[PDB]
Length: 137
Ligand SMILES: *C/C=C(C)/C=C/C=C1/N(C)c2ccccc2C1(C)C
Image 1 (tube, rainbow, N blue to C red):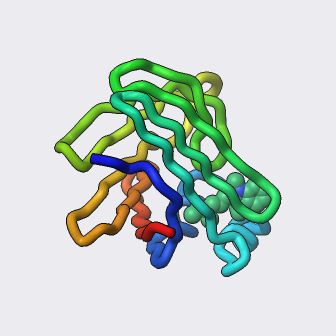
Image 2 (tube, rainbow, N blue to C red):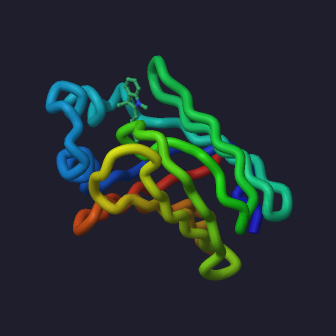
């Protein structure tokens, strides 16, 4: 299920509420939802080994994981945590995260390559769920 490729975000719901739930400074919340801050996603997939890059205006995040192999990473609000990714179907994977230090909401995310060629991502902080929808390029 080649998640590989370069991804262009074309929709995003409930994102500010997610940040709000996580505790994100209001000023950062407002800049976070600007048409300028739209993230670009590059995924590089081979087997159970994944490389995903997320790039905004002045920041980038790189993660490297194997499905099943626990790894270190950051939440959405950038808190250090341990993560573990598993398959849900052929075209879906889900990742649960465990805060390294401190304690806050229960976070996670999922990734879903559809049949109409889209890539759906969800992110969850406790009750609240954010969906974002990507296309290739
Ligand atoms: C949908 C995902 C979004 C809008 C990602 C936002 C992420 C960031 N990051 C990581 C960042 C770092 C510095 C300054 C601004 C940001 C922004 C809020 C765009």
